[PDB]
Image 1: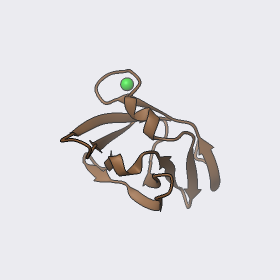
Image 2 (image 1 turned 90 degrees about the horizontal axis):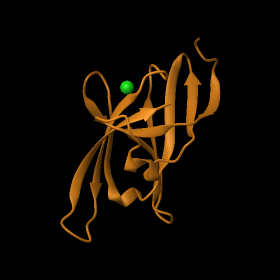
Image 3 (image 1 turned 180 degrees about the vertical axis):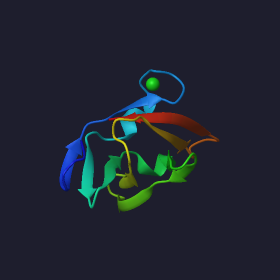
Image 4 (image 1 turned 135 degrees about the horizontal axis):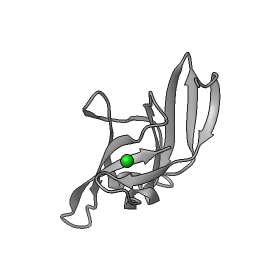
Length: 116
Ligand SMILES: [Cl-]
């Protein structure tokens, strides 16, 4: 059941945090993600669109949301690559996104789930 070391692509979709429905956050998170399996551990990374608007992206780690790691940024196309470890790919991962639209007092939070 445990994946061999190496790099893979893994498709994913985003559900709403509290409903079994597709989340609007799908448009910002590019599937497939990259899965890096190294020394048993599993690291997921993927590109985020409209990066400047996605002020915060956290995933739940030990019953608490923690900011994801930024591996790189591309200011030209307004994207960035985020990364986090996932212990169990068969489970839905809880996440939180803070969306900021400066063109107007607009600052809202989205609860989401990653489905691999
Ligand atoms: Cl469920």
